[PDB]
Length: 127
Ligand SMILES: Cc1cc2c(-c3cncc(N)c3)cnc(N[C@@H]3CCNC[C@H]3OCC3CCS(=O)(=O)CC3)c2[nH]c1=O
Picture 1 (cartoon, rainbow, N blue to C red):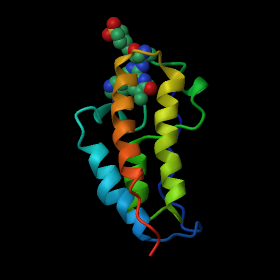
Picture 2: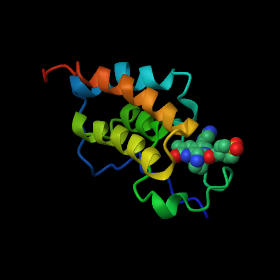
Picture 3: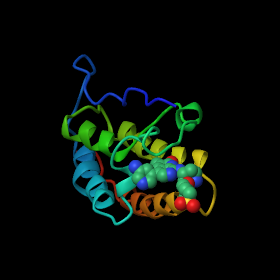
C-alpha cells in the first residue's frame, strides 16, 4: 500500500546521447501528449496512497509515467529512441494491465496512445 521510490531520471555513469530522434521524442511526441486534455493522470507517478490503490504496486512492477519521461528527456537520460519509446509503451501497458476495459483511465490512455502511434510512425531517420 506504500509508494515505491520513483523511477530514476538521473544516472551519471549511464552513457547518454542527444540524437535527432530523441529530440523528436521531446519536441513532438512528449509535447503533444503532455498538452492533451487526458494527460493529467499520467503526468506523475501513480500515488497509490492518495488514490487509495493499495494493490497498484503489487500488480505494476515496472511503473512509468510522462513526468518521469519528461525528466529523462530534459536531462538527457537516454542513449537511443528505443529506450524512450519503451517507456511510453510501459506506461500504456501498465494502465491496461491494472484497470478494466471501459474504465475512464483506459479510454484516456487509448486516446494518448493513438496520438503516440501517429507521431512514432513519422520518427525521422538517424542523422
Ligand atoms: C494511471 C492510473 C491512474 C488512475 C487514477 C488517477 C486519476 N486521476 C489522477 C491520477 N494521478 C490517477 C485513478 N484510478 C485508477 N484506477 C481505479 C481503479 C481501477 N478502475 C479505474 C479506477 O477506478 C476509480 C473508480 C472509483 C469509484 S467511481 O468514482 O464510482 C468510478 C471510478 C487509476 N489507474 C491507473 O492506472
